Image: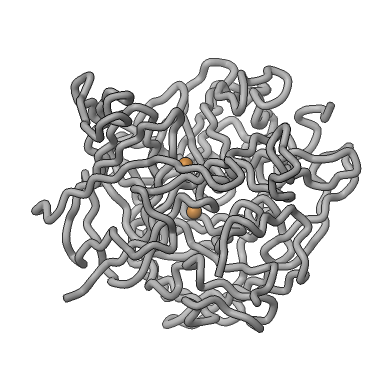
Amino acid sequence: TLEKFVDALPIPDTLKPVQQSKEKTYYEVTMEECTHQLHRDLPPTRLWGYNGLFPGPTIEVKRNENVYVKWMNNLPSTHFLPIDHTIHHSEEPEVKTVVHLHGGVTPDDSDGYPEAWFSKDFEQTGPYFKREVYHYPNQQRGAILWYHDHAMALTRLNVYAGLVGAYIIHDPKEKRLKLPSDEYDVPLLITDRTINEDGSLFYPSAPENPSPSLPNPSIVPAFCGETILVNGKVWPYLEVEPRKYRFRVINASNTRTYNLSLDNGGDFIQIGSDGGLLPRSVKLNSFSLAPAERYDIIIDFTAYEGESIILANSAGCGGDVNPETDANIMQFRVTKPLAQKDESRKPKYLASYPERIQNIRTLKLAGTQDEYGRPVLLLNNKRWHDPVTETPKVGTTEIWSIINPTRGTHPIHLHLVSFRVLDRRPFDIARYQESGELSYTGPAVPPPPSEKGWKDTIQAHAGEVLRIAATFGPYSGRYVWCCHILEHEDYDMMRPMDITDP
Ligand SMILES: [Cu+2]
Ligand SMILES: [Cu+2]
C-alpha cells in the first residue's frame, strides 16, 4: 500500500536548554500525547512523544558537560496500546514511565532503572525512584547514544508508542579529524511500525491463534512491523549534497534486526560503534544492526550527483524480506546544491585502540513456560525479581561468557559500561540442553572489524558462546543488563547488575 519515498526525512531539532551556565546545563523534557502524520497518505497518528515530538528532540552535549534533564510525565492515565497485566506482580498506576539514556556513563539513580518509574507529575513512584532531575556528567567518549522509556513491564509498549530520541556526545578533541559535521551529520532513528488505515498504530493484543484461557491482552514474544520509518516518517527520502555525510544510524525498533546496504552496491565507511569512534575506519558494503545498536558511518555521495540511492535491507522479520516493503529503509536523492566546499574528511586513523581479569562470568540465555504456555525468556535461569547474581566489583575487569542455546539472536546490553568483544565460538546445542556440558564444535572467531572498538549492545547469536570484557565503573550502584528485544525484556529477559564498592 503506502507509496515509498514521497515524504522528506525529518531531522529532529536540537533541544534548547531551559537554563545554561559554564557549570551546569539544564533541560526539561515532558512526555505528551501528540499527533503527527507519518506518511503523505495517512491520517495523523496519535503517539506519545518526548516534548510531543516523534522522535524526541535530539540532545547534543559536550564530553564532560555537566548536564541535567528533568524528564516529566504528562501522559494520560490509560494506555492506548494493549497492556498485559499478567506478566508482572507486586495499587500502582497503569501508565508508568522512566527514561534510560542508553549508553550513558550515568550515576545509578539517573540510569532509568525499571522500578524507578513515575506516573504523571511524579504522583506515584516506583520502589527504586530517587530523583526527578537526572544527572548526566558525560565523562565518556564522544558517541551516539539514545534515550528511551524503560518502565517495568511496559518498555515494549512505551517505546512503540514513540518514546525514543537521539543523544550525541561531542568530544572537542575529535574536531581536528574534520569528520562531516553540522548539517552534514544526521541521525537516522529506524523504527518499524504497523499502521491501521485510520492512521492509528497497530500493536498486537495477542499472538496468532490464542486460546480463550490465554490472557487478553497477551504479550507476544516478537514484533515485526509492516512498514519502516526513519525519523518518524514512513519510507522517506533525503535530498543530499554530492559530498560526504556522517550518519548516526540507530536501531530504535522493538525486535527487528536490519542488514543494511546501498542498492547501487556502493560502500559505507564505518567510523564508530556504540561506544565511540573505532580505532580505524572500516570500509563496508553492508552491516547488521540489531535493536539498540548504533553505527556511526560516512556515506560519500561525491561521485553520485543526481542519483537516487536506496538504503536497503536484506534481513527478514518473521519471514523473508519483502522487496516492496521492508527491504526498503529510505532513499537518498543526490540533488541538493553544494552549500560550500566539502572540507570534511574520511580519515583512516580515528582513535587509539581499546589490565587484570578479576572474574569470568558464565551466563546462559534460555526460556521457561508460564501457566498459559507462553515463553518466558530469562537471563541465567533467574527472574528479574530474584536476588541479584551479577555483582561485579567497581574498578575491576571481567570476562562475560554468554551461552546462547536458543534458536535466535539476542542483542545483549550492559548498562553503565562499554565493553570489548573477544570472540564467538559455536557449540553443541543438544548436548548443552541435555547435560549442561559445553562442547565446542569449532574454533573461536574474533570479532569483525566493526566490533573491534567499544560496544554496549551486542548480538549473541544462536548456538554460540560470545565472550566480552568490561571494566566496571567509574560509578558503583544498582544497574541492569538485559536483552534489547523489548518483547523479551519485558517477560522477563532483564536482570539487576550491582557494581559493588567494598
Ligand atoms: Cu536501551
Ligand atoms: Cu532476547
In this rendering, the answer to whether 74 lies above or below 395 is below
Quadrant position of residue 123: bottom right
Quadrant position of residue 324: top right
- Closer to the camera in the image, 426 or 397: 426
Residue 205 position in % (x across, y down): 74, 46
For the rendered model, the colour scheme is one colour
Residue 278 position in % (x across, y down): 32, 41
- The count of marks equals 0
Left or right of 358 on screen, residue 7? right
- Closer to the camera in the image, 321 or 54: 321
Residue 154 position in % (x across, y down): 61, 59
Going 46% across and 37% down the picture, which residue do you hit? 297
Going 68% across and 48% down the picture, which residue do you hit? 218
From this viewpoint, which residue is outermost toward the left? 356
Using the rendered image of the protein, determine whether residue 189 is visible from the camera's viewpoint.
no
Left or right of 294 on screen, residue 326? right
Quadrant position of residue 445: top left
In this rendering, the answer to whether 114 lies above or below 414 is below
Going 77% across and 28% down the picture, which residue do you hit? 4
In this rendering, the answer to whether 361 lies above or below 63 is above
- Closer to the camera in the image, 22 or 99: 99
Going 56% across and 72% down the picture, which residue do you hit? 117
Left or right of 432 on screen, residue 124? right
Using the rendered image of the protein, determine whether residue 502 is visible from the camera's viewpoint.
yes
Quadrant of the image containing the C terminus = bottom left
Residue 308 position in % (x across, y down): 67, 23
Quadrant of the image containing the N terminus = top right
